[PDB]
Amino acid sequence: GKITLYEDRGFQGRHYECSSDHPNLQPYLSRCNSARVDSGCWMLYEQPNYSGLQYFLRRGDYADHQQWMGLSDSVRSCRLIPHSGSHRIRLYEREDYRGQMIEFTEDCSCLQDRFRFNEIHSLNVLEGSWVLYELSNYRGRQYLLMPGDYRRYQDWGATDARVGSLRRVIDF
Image 1 (tube, helix red, strand yellow):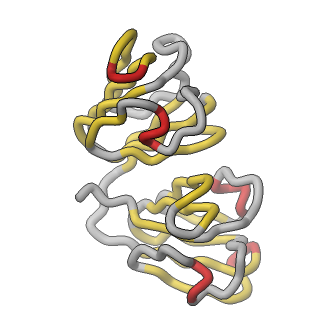
Image 2 (tube, rainbow, N blue to C red; image 1 turned 60 degrees about the vertical axis):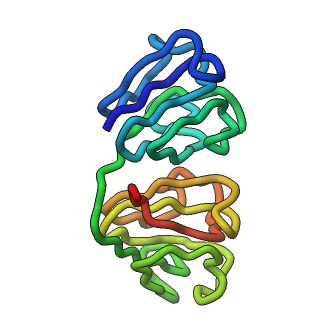
């Protein structure tokens, strides 16, 4: 993967190119207001060490922070998300893999259609990476999920268990 991050809008100003995860961009960028993703799937984070608000970007040009749904020009770390040809996730009503479970292998724009709860309290990512969204139709806060177990909502970087939708990280 390859991303170039620019301080100013429209790909202007000081920039930094990443081909790997970077946990602290402060030495290289004072702000980030545009991005060119040459290849790969990336998660940008507001704070260092993959913390704070998260934003998913894929191949293409983002001329201002709003183009990645950003709320500010704060980008202080970034992660390269591995590709996967298959996706499978189990979502649970209660913490520690209890309560109602539903398994997804495809995107879901309204979680509440079938998973009739407004919160997800634990989940197991069996295959592929996914983005969880606070609100329906892929809106609100984003939380990246990668293969492994998540026993509580704090484990995916959220401050509450509300989820409205979820989609696979795909590069096509």
